[PDB]
Amino acid sequence: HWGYGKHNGPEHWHKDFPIAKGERQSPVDIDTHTAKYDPSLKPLSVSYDQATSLRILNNGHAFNVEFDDSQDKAVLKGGPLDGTYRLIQFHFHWGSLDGQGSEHTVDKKKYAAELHLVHWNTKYGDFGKAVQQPDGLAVLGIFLKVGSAKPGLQKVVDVLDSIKTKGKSADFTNFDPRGLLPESLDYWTYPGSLTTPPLLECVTWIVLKEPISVSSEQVLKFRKLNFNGEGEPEELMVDNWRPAQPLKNRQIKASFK
Ligand SMILES: [Zn+2]
């Protein structure tokens, strides 16, 4: 099955998922000097005050914090979006070393990790219908650099020992995702895809310019997770990131100048 090793990694995915070579694949390198400032873009509206987290789960390629998405509780609006997008989960991509780990890059610069908050368009009724549509998903991407600790991340870091192996899940209630956001909400946006199989081209990417800082100790704990299931040989969950894909016929827009 697909993964991030030498024999099943991203360079192999096209054999099972031929859209891997499609026209709007993600991630991409953000060239800050060719991105177009678009003054018609609106500020992002992030309404997470009523967010209800439920569970944290190791799915064999990352860990997902899942939210109750049966009502408009935690929603993303504005920016380049039409309509209302509900938060369903967030997860991260990270490296084996501090110098790599993000999926998107900025002027070819790699960050130590990348946070993805995944939202789906309410007009489509459920997540599974949203993935089939070109405007079905909105993913907020936030870079992580190593520096000072992020206090609002620590609750996540402390529970990772209970979900070390694939298929492990733990109750994870009352987590506030507002603790993960940077000060500024300036962003780049472009139309893209999921960055894991099935790689569907259903995503409006919204990548924040300002990274958040996490401590060396916090990212170290990410790297103690396991791709494998319990009772299988240990393969550390590191470098679960897809390399940048060709931009092709797309334009990256910026909310700022
Ligand atoms: Zn992701």
Image: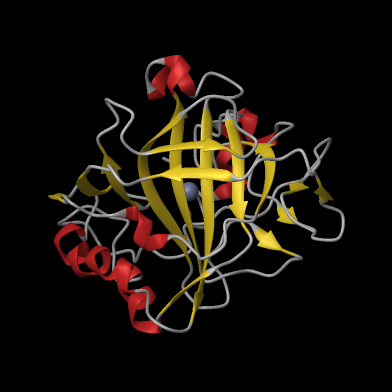
Q: Position of residue 140 (x, y in %)?
A: 52, 47
Number of numbered discs on residues: 0
Seen at 35% across and 42% down, the residue is: 89
**Which of the 4 image quarters holds residue 68?**
top left
Seen at 63% across and 29% down, the residue is: 19
From the viewer's perspective, is 111 left or right of 147? right
Q: Which quadrant is home to the N terminus?
A: top left
Q: Is residue 143 visible?
A: yes
Q: Is residue 202 above or below residue 98?
A: above
Q: Position of residue 139 (x, y in %)?
A: 52, 42
From the viewer's perspective, is 91 left or right of 43? left
From the viewer's perspective, is 40 left or right of 71? right
Q: How is the image coloured?
A: secondary structure
Q: Which quadrant is home to the C terminus?
A: bottom right
Q: Is residue 240 above or below residue 202?
A: below
Seen at 61% across and 36% down, the residue is: 204
Q: Is residue 40 above or below residue 72?
A: below
Q: Is residue 2 visible?
A: no
Q: Position of residue 85 (x, y in %)?
A: 46, 31
Q: Residue furthest right?
A: 34
Nearer the observer, 103 or 124: 124
Seen at 50% across and 64% down, the residue is: 182
Q: Is residue 156 above or below residue 229?
A: below
Q: Position of residue 107 (x, y in %)?
A: 76, 65
From the viewer's perspective, is 255 left or right of 166? right
Nearer the observer, 235 or 186: 186
